[PDB]
Amino acid sequence: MPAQTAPPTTANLNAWLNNFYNAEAKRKSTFPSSLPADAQPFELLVINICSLSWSDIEAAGLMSHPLWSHFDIEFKNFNSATSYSGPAAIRLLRASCGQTSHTNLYQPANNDCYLFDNLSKLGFTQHLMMGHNGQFGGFLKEVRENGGMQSELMDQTNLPVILLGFDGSPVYDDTAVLNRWLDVTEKDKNSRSATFYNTLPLHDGNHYPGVSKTADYKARAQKFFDELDAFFTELEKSGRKVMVVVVPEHGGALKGDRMQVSGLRDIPSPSITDVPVGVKFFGMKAPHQGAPIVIEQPSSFLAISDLVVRVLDGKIFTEDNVDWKKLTSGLPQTAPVSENSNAVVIQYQDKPYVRLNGGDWVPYPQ
Ligand SMILES: [Mg+2]
Ligand SMILES: [Zn+2]
Image (cartoon, rainbow, N blue to C red; front, side, top):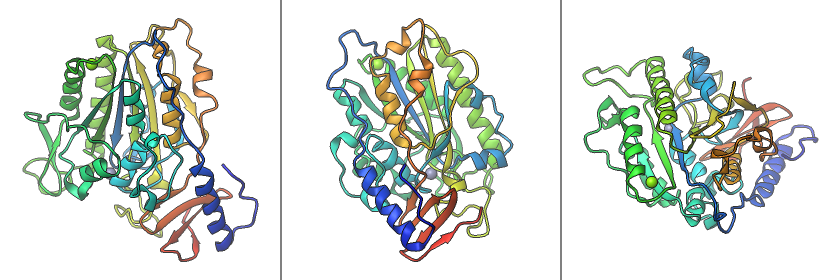
C-alpha cells in the first residue's frame, strides 16, 4: 500500500493508480516447488458468491446471521476489485498475482498467477462447480478463457432447483450442490482437491418457480446463509479435512447512492466491493475456539492465495497447538482499488473517487 501524501488532484490520483498497478505487478503469491513428504492432504473449497457485500447484508438485516460467527478467520475490509461477475471470478482465479487493471484480466497472465493451477502442481485435483449453468453474461466462458479453469463442470443432473434466473435458467439448491461436492471429492481418487464453486442465488432477477416478481433478497440470503452454515455443521461431522474460503464476487448493490441507483453496478463503488470474506478449517485436531479472528487491514485476493500457501502442508489439521496469530499475521495488504470496463474506484486519503472513461476523478458519495 503506497503513499497518498500528495493532495488529491485528478493528475495525482491518475499517478497514484499507475503507481498502484506498477507496485501490484511485482507481487506474487509464491508456492513451494513440492509438498513435504509428510504433508496432510485436505480439500480446499472456494465458495464464490454473487451479489453479496457487507452493505447488502446490513440492508437485509443479516449482519448477525450465525454464519458470520462460524468462521475461523474473517476479513473485515476485503475488496472485490470489481462489481461484475466475470471479472470477479477472473480476479479470484488469478489470486496468486498482484491486482491488474480490468483490461489485463482479458490478457494472458503468468501461469503462476492462477491459484488452482498452482495447487494442481502440488497435486490438488481441480473441480469446477456451479449452482447454475454459467451461460448468462458469458460467465462460464470467461472462467475458462480468462480464468484458465478448464475442468469439466461438475455434474448438475437431478439437482433440485430453488430459483429461476432472469433468463429462465436454473438456480440449484446450494445444500444439494454442496452435498454432491462431498461425494464427488470422495470419489475423485485423490486425497486432496481444490474446488472453485460459483453460486448466485442472490442475483438480481432470480425468482421462485411460478412467481414472476424477483424473490425477496433477504429471504434468499437467509436461506443461503442457513444452508452454508448447516453445511459447515455437516462438514464438521464428516471428520474430513477441509479449508473453506467464502469470497463474494461483489455486492448486489441493494443500497444505492447519489451517483448510482440501487441495483446498478456500472461503477464498482465502495459499498458494492466491500465484501465479507471468511475462512473456516474443518477436521482439525484442535479446531479454532471462540469468535472469528478478524483481519482488519485492507485485503484482497492476494491474501487468500498467501493464506492457502501457509497451510499447503496440511499440518494445521493435525497440530495440537495451532499458532493462529502467526497464521493470520503479516498477510499481504492490498489497497481498495476497483475496476470495471472504463470505471475505476479508489480510496485516496480515506475518501473514495471514481474515474469514468478517463475523465476527471470525481469524489464519490460517502
Ligand atoms: Mg478425493
Ligand atoms: Zn455476480
